[PDB]
Length: 300
Length: 307
Length: 6
Ligand SMILES: [Mn+2]
Ligand SMILES: [Mn+2]
Ligand SMILES: [Mn+2]
Ligand SMILES: [Mn+2]
Image 1 (spheres, each protein chain N blue to C red):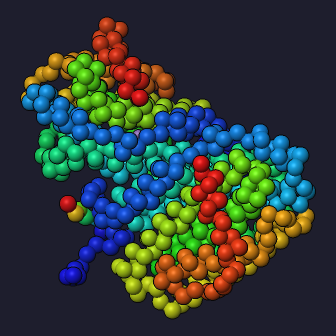
Image 2 (image 1 turned 90 degrees about the vertical axis):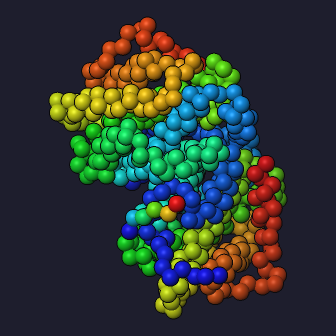
């Protein structure tokens, strides 16, 4: 049978590599109640400039825009790939996304941004972000396996692998270079690991579909993906202007963030056999090479 | 004090994430989070040596069949909890749903492991050769038939039976049998860890189910009508008959020292009644005193084998 | 029915 065909018997798994992803989540398991942010609030109050406060605030608002929501994609993958192991993968990632929504909802509460979050659609660049995220997710529930596969590609490479990562990076720069917001940075680092596992899980599925239905990856599909990515990267660049609306900060630069995102996209596209779009030079993408090491450091 | 003239129901879709209309959901998700476990934590070498050297055929067969019976429910795609948000479209119920659904995959992987470890994959594949198991499949299919029903009254019925039977009772005789080996003979300690942890999980799922049933009570009291309550009473009665016969198959090679069928049957009947009380439904069995205290050690042993 | 509440 194919990846789209229902198997009744639990084991053996047809796609046993699913367990590498579920085991990674299991090993990385965390909940927000493990962290207290009192010390972070004190530093925010006493030791951050207006520019810095606004970058922290807007970065968290941007994260919440994606994370504080019902995210139904992963919980529904079993409807498209009706295998016991993909119900497992889906349920593990879905639960994970609930731990995320609770974590970012708490950060909003603790920092006093619940009113601003409710009014976030007043920000023009955010409305453009809602449109592209909607575009990506629109065929999430389509019975047309080709339509859905585009949703899956764009969900994995953009939404899981890229959309949030500039905000993660901004928040981690405070801890790395100034030693502030250590606990926020714990949450961020754990979320970044989870989301990398989600994106890689999506890449794994996409490549299984490519092995079994190479015809789905046609010229129209590849062109749609590349254009949507280009439009979305332009939107996330403008997000950066709003995050830094009160001024540039010392710990991280917008230019470096844009190259970071462009680089992350290309690497994902390579992994699923789609032509690179930006071709970022080594000296540009090395600027935020510290990201991975900071994520690892703040994982404990 | 002042009741609302109108309000959105549990079946309507709230779009904004917080505040939660049903904040108590978090009691159940936090209990699961706190009890979090996977089978990879556990090594069964000692248990297999215990099994090999120190258990009789009657005992081995009780262990094997209790595990095949647990596996029959656990080693499967269990899509109920992952599906509840389709019926109660609230952010909090997606979180409860997702939390219990992931838990059930930790369960399926755990019992799949025990089957491979104990060498019972062949017996599991052919489990439908056992008559009493085919009858268990029938009563389970009746509970589960309106799981995906758009008709809310019927779905509510599925949920009641799902919670009081499948989550709260159907497994618990097997859990008790396996635990008895540790409590009374100090064998199978690691297996009993897995079972104790599963027991804790399934109690939380049943109580979460019960919470949801009680919220539906408040919002739609007209749903708990005469026919519906009677439909539940009858299905429960039948189900307990099948699970009694499951015991006869589990002990097919003879009765064992650490636990007895009659005590187990009164244990099941009792916990059914308690779950009925909790959703304001009249008791069915009305067990004792002092039958059901035969297995009053259950919870203590569960608490003990969780480390 | 879809709706908001705070
Ligand atoms: Mn997330
Ligand atoms: Mn994710
Ligand atoms: Mn279970
Ligand atoms: Mn359960």
